[PDB]
Image (cartoon, rainbow, N blue to C red; front, side, top):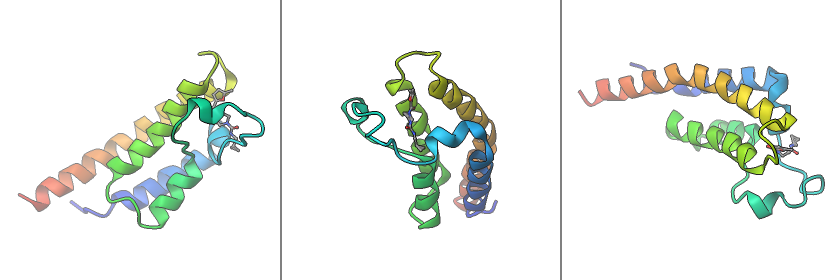
Length: 119
Ligand SMILES: Cc1ccc(C(=O)N2CCN(C(=O)NCC3CC3)CC2)o1
């Protein structure tokens, strides 16, 4: 029932994600120089460094907010991909499955802790 525990749990999960080879395309912004049409398709860029920096700045109030930004990394990859069998998109799907597997307890525990608080 620790209302703050999600933050370190998310730091730990981001550490795991940064060690995963599948995260390499998503660790930093799109060199618009290598993908010049990227911002014609993607309205709101997002990367794992921005997520980690937002978390470390204390600019997430809840793990739901972090989860929304991580899911935006994956929806951007799905929107930008020319093919459902594009190398980078395929890496996004594996990393998304890994993230969802790990974030599910973080969200459950946070929401349970907040319910216990306002019991
Ligand atoms: C061909 C294809 C399909 C889907 C995607 C995709 O999701 N992209 C675009 C390319 N990518 C980078 O250029 N990232 C480089 C920074 C990490 C240094 C960002 C993510 O790209």
